[PDB]
Image (tube, coloured by chain):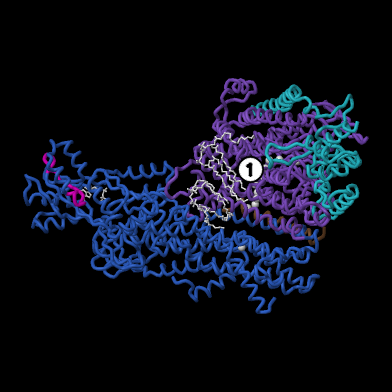
Amino acid sequence: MSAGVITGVLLVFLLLGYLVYALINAE
Amino acid sequence: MAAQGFLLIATFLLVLMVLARPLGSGLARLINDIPLPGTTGVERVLFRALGVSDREMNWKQYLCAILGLNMLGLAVLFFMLLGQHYLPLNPQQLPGLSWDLALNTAVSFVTNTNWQSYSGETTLSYFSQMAGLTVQNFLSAASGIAVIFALIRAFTRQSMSTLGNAWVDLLRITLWVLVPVALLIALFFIQQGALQNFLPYQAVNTVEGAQQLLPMGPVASQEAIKMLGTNGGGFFNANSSHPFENPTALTNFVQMLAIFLIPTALCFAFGEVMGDRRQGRMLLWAMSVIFVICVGVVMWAEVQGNPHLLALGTDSSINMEGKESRFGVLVSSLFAVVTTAASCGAVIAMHDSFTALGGMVPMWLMQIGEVVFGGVGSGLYGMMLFVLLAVFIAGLMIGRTPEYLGKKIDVREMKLTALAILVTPTLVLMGAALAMMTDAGRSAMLNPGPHGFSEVLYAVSSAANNNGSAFAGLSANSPFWNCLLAFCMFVGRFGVIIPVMAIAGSLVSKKSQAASSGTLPTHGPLFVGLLIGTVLLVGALTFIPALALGPVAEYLS
Amino acid sequence: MSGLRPALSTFIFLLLITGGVYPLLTTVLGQWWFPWQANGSLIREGDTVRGSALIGQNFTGNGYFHGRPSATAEMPYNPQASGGSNLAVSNPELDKLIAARVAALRAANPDASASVPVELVTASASGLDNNITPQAAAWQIPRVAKARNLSVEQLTQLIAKYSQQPLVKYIGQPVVNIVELNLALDKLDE
Amino acid sequence: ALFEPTLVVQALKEAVKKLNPQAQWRNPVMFIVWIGSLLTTCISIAMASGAMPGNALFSAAISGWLWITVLFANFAEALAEGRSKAQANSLKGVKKTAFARKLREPKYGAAADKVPADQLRKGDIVLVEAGDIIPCDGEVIEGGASVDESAITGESAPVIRESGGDFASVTGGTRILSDWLVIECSVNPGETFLDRMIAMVEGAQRRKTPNEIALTILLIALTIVFLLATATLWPFSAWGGNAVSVTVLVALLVCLIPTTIGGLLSAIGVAGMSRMLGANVIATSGRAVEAAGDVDVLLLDKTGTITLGNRQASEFIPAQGVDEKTLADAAQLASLADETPEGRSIVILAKQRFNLRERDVQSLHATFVPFTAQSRMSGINIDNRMIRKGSVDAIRRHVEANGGHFPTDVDQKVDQVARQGATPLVVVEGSRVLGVIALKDIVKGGIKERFAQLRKMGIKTVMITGDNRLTAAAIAAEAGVDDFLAEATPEAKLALIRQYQAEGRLVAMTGDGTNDAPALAQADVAVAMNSGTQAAKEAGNMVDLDSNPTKLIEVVHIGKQMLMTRGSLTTFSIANDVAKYFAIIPAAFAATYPQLNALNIMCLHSPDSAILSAVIFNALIIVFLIPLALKGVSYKPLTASAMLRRNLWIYGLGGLLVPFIGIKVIDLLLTVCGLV
Ligand SMILES: CCCCCCCCCCCCCCCCCC(=O)OC[C@H](COP(=O)([O-])OCC(O)COP(=O)([O-])OC[C@@H](COC(=O)CCCCCCCCCCCCCCCCC)OC(=O)CCCCCCCCCCCCCCCCC)OC(=O)CCCCCCCCCCCCCCCCC
Ligand SMILES: CCCCCCCCCCCCCCCCCC(=O)OC[C@H](COP(=O)([O-])OCC(O)COP(=O)([O-])OC[C@@H](COC(=O)CCCCCCCCCCCCCCCCC)OC(=O)CCCCCCCCCCCCCCCCC)OC(=O)CCCCCCCCCCCCCCCCC
Ligand SMILES: Nc1ncnc2c1ncn2[C@@H]1O[C@H](COP(=O)(O)OP(=O)(O)O)[C@@H](O)[C@H]1O
Ligand SMILES: [K+]
Ligand SMILES: [K+]
Ligand SMILES: [K+]
Ligand SMILES: [K+]
Ligand SMILES: [K+]
Ligand SMILES: [K+]
Ligand SMILES: [K+]
Ligand SMILES: [K+]
Ligand SMILES: [K+]
Ligand SMILES: [K+]
Ligand SMILES: [K+]
Ligand SMILES: [K+]
């Protein structure tokens, strides 16, 4: 909807990707 | 009223427990690869004719078999719905479906969800209804029961790699559990008054002089399988509210019995296959306690009903809006809880017209993952995921290795259990957020405010949780809603089926170690309460903010 | 590669069974055993179909028994667009419709109670409800008796004649068939 | 090592300020909290100068308390690591220096050489005297005296070491008392089990156990669902009314995710390893310690492990054709060469009580027959009498091979010897049987109570003996074990390992012999003894420094404590979130949904005060539960269901109740202080 919403969605997707990476590759 | 509700719950649960035990023994015989009495010979020559050998696949080929059958059914049903104006049995000359509606209906009937963003009697022809929709009602149920057959075989098998024959399991389930029981149920429905013919739409001269066109078609044959396979795909837009689908109270009682029949029989079969019936009784005690609490809450909410009725001159505040008059509010509440806990899309009553609490508890019952008899097979392996979570927690709190039914719970099974738990709330939350940031997702709302958010959340939860029941006030016939919901159904079915089969392939290789003095009894009231607390607490901590912005806000309004 | 053939064979066999044998056997057995209630439960006088015994028709006449409101598209009690209003409790449209229905029913039934039965002001789930409670029928007796020049005793007897009850009192509700009630009223008049 | 020393706290707080940048992303929950803290800090800076919200003080307080939450979690982890490092550095401060007496020839008194510590390798021979620090670990090849192992074990009473016997190896950094011990080096310095444990502790690169990995996966999944709910709350309220502020969403997300267990997991692991070190047990890794909480059978060697060893001749029953001054001579001729402590005791007491010291010990034609565990033979063919001795079965086998037979008096005599628990041993000339020499063994002492505690734990303790069946029964009844296994070859112990592992039952064992290396290699728990040899210590995953057989009690205690602390803190963290909802959700939705204020069952003052109180409780619960994670949970031996019920009633109900009181008290303190 706006630049702030785009930044928030991107940050949430990056955090989700990091958490899924940590779950899959939990050494 | 409370006495009538207690009598209804007690009678329903008693008849269900009586009926599901011989079916539990039959399903245990099907799990143990033992042919049913009288099926020997004809089953062998049928397997020889079909070309299925005595092979026994592992988890990878079993999952590939289930996924390939589901994708083939998806393609066949999609092309059948897209080109339904060339196929026969079309007396109304109904045109072919749009691409988005056909894709949504195909994914909906393959993923055992049976969401319907259309009116059946206006949209679909008889051949489509009895040849794609009914065959997918059979096939999705058979696929779910085959997956739970693989999981039960993985729990009972000792240090092997194979998981049974997937085609043999599907054929055995469909031919000896689905078809004859649905034949009996359909014949009883026809006797009570349900519709089964192929006549064109009958013209009616109304007494006062109007003209109404009565829809026809093979309603009862699809009604029996939508009850039996926890399918809930209505022949008409009214679904089980329609008198041609559910004419009588006895018919509706048989409907609820058929909805809970196969999950309860699968729990009994699991307990009998593992030898310890206390495990199946523990699972059934957990689902029954949660179910009884939810039913009592929903009947209390619906009996409280609309508070404005006495203000606007009415006999009682009984919420009869959007409920059929041949069924009480107690019966409607019970059916609502049964279908929204059992991953069935059938509605005796419009859930949109329910009160705030009586819409929250069905929607929360979908949102917790459909573990209270939550569909044929799907409820049992979702409950298995919650059981692995609970035994991990219990093993941690007792200081021993995480253990369930003699088999160790290790890092790989925790990874796959976590992913399978993660799939459906992720879909619900992201799909609801995507619908709530879009004008195409917000313009489908009918009621304004918190109940409109409840409509959107209910639609996304039923799509992702393979339920299919709707408030139906949402206008989900847009291409955006069709594609979003189809994605939700596809992922919420198959991305939960895949890690469950991976758990099964991880658990076949292990050996069920015998019990000892220090082992934890995975039964009894302590573990029943622990599993109930785990399920309710996980679902609550996932979905209380959504309920607070929806139905809780509507209740506190 | 030796795995596609079992998939196709199983799919074609199961599709053929569950789409041309189970529905065919169901239709054949239904038409052989329960033909009237398998073909529509149609109430036919002569060669004219006056309505199914399950669907229910829109009755707005003074001399007839009025059923529950219908929220189907186009005309009320339209079987081509079955479905409820899907109106929430918090929706002001439901309150407006309930107020309008209460006012209309109070105007139509002056010689009755001021507390209207809830099913007469609340729309049904399907929009094709052929049933109301005997309490609602008893509420509507004075208007029908005044319009038809009948008596309360005969109206109660006829309502009890066309009343249906479940096997046990908690799996359903006692209901009366409105369409057959109105056909019985017409046949009694002539 | 105390509970919270001042210097440890003040140094590891600086460590906490040093483990901010890149020590956070290894932990996913705390990296989420760190990212939220940074985002709220930037949001507060924007609110101060450059963003249209003006409540910069509230966002600054939220960001500061999130940073405090990260600081307290790192304080827990750093305090555990600092305590472990302090214990390892205190154990490191031995007097092991460059003072040594290298010998080119292994005889006593060789050249009086001086070599440094770095000039030592796998093969070397060193000499020590009275009051000398041991340079390197190794078996003793000549001499024997008392070795004071106080600086390593933590307790006095010097142990008696014998040249090549049961007490052969010597621990480094330990003083030598009385006589000398000529010591051959086994493993080069720097490569010692103590050195590996010290290197594992200092510079903590500790590997996560599989249980910790699975719990981390579960916490990650909970973080994912809480992040999804928090992220999706913005459009859900944005459509309904005014959108909820980002700082309140971040505060709710941090309050929701398993912050307590997610910040205390490493503290629990390191504190469990430190408590293992404090029980005088060295562990290679936490995997064995956590597996020890699942074992159900413990295997035991008799001599050395369950008894002190050093068997001595007590009764010395002769035969009819032996009388006197012949059995002692035969025993001395059979035992003058074998290098076993019971043989040396027999040698030094037989001549003592029979005045037969005039017999020469060297006669230039000695066969020098060693002792083998499976053969059970010892003796020197010195005058064509070919004298031998051994166990009862070995004597019967050797008599049935060359000699005629044996009468019933030998069986009666060995039964009478085994009546009081001493193991039978009889000498034979080769064609005729002789008298039976007893070998008294002393039980280690107060072990019946500890074996009763093992039985109460559900661990079926069983001791593998060899020796003779009846004396094994006598010593098993005296010790208090559940079962025994006599007449055992060294292969039979590995056979018992594989038989117990074939059932799926997890097997633990203790041993101190050099013939137990495959047993400790295949065993899941392989607790060695400090009196054991270097090969057994290297083959074992754990070694006990107390030389105690029933140290598995403390090992099971610590492993179960670690697992139950992890599970209990996870349950507490999950159960806190319903009170987090009841504190935040009516506070978060106050302008977009003022109708949700009925959910404020805690009767909190303001929405900002409620959110701040939830964040303050989330920050303070970690520092309040640091002592619980450091000490572990209170482990009591009960049944599994009763223990689960007690842990649930005291932790799940605690997480249901305690956050309500905590948030309410914090809100009242803020109200009476006037901050909000
Ligand atoms: C309020 C808060 C929450 C409430 C919590 C309540 C939750 C619900 C509870 C239900 C949980 C289910 C348990 C798991 C399944 C158990 C199945 C089983 O094997 O059972 C044996 C099981 C273990 O015993 P066992 O001796 O080890 O037996 C094992 C052997 O394998 C078996 O040995 P056997 O073969 O010798 O035994 C005989 C044989 C029986 O014989 C047979 O083989 C069957 C065939 C008989 C012939 C058929 C004709 C007659 C049958 C009639 C029905 C069919 C025809 C009907 C006709 C209509 C057509 C459709 O076994 C069976 O088949 C048993 C199955 C039937 C009984 C199960 C009843 C469970 C439901 C209880 C009623 C609902 C209560 C709660 C609801 C209300 C709450 C609001 O025991 C039980 O029965 C457990 C259930 C106990 C009753 C629950 C009572 C709960 C409390 C009541 C509510 C009061 C509080 C409310 C407060 C009010 C405020 C509003
Ligand atoms: C937040 C934590 C809260 C506190 C936690 C503390 C837990 C302890 C609570 C104690 C207080 C309760 C006292 C009331 C007495 C009633 C129960 C009783 O008798 O035993 C007490 C029982 C301990 O039983 P036990 O250790 O197995 O052994 C004692 C038994 O008496 C011996 O029985 P058995 O082992 O010999 O086997 C039973 C036997 C039969 O033998 C007997 O019991 C003796 C003979 C009596 C005849 C009656 C049996 C026939 C059944 C007819 C009706 C039964 C009652 C149905 C009413 C249910 C209504 C709700 O036959 C059976 O196997 C029958 C099937 C067993 C099920 C029967 C009842 C199940 C329903 C009750 C639990 C469901 C509601 C809990 C909701 C809580 C959720 C938060 O404690 C509980 O019931 C615990 C319930 C509460 C647990 C809460 C845990 C929540 C989870 C934590 C949060 C999530 C964790 C984080 C995970 C997230 C992942 C990231
Ligand atoms: N020095 C010795 N001379 C002769 N026989 C011995 C000697 N030491 C032990 N034995 C015999 O060996 C048997 C025990 O063997 P083993 O267990 O391998 O040695 P240990 O008991 O020292 O561990 C005993 O029955 C004993 O008779
Ligand atoms: K469904
Ligand atoms: K549906
Ligand atoms: K869930
Ligand atoms: K699920
Ligand atoms: K789920
Ligand atoms: K599901
Ligand atoms: K389903
Ligand atoms: K599921
Ligand atoms: K499902
Ligand atoms: K979840
Ligand atoms: K989860
Ligand atoms: K927390």
Give the quarter of the image for residue B383: top right
Give the quarter of the image for residue D400: top left
Colour in which the image shows chain A? brown
Look at the numbered disc 1 and say if its residue's Cβ is closer than 8 Å to ligand 12. Answer: no
Q: Look at the image and give the residue range highlighted in magenta.
A: D417-433
Would residue B221 be seen by someone viewing this image from the given angle? no
Q: Residue D293, percent across and down?
A: 44, 54
- Given the current orientation, which residue lies at the most extreme bottom position? D673
Relative to the observer, which residue lies in front, B356 or B121?
B356
Vertical placement of residue D207 versus D77, above or below: above
Q: Residue C56, percent across and down?
A: 84, 37
Q: Chain of mark 1?
A: B
Vertical placement of residue D503 versus D633, above or below: above
* Figure chain in cyan: C
Q: Residues within 10 Å of mark 1 (few under 14, many from 20)?
A: many
Relative to the observer, which residue lies in front, D339 or D124?
D339
- Name which residue type carries label 1: Phe
Task: Look at the numbered disc 1 and give the secondary structure of its residue.
Answer: loop
Vertical placement of residue D185 versus B388, above or below: below
Colour in which the image shows chain D? blue
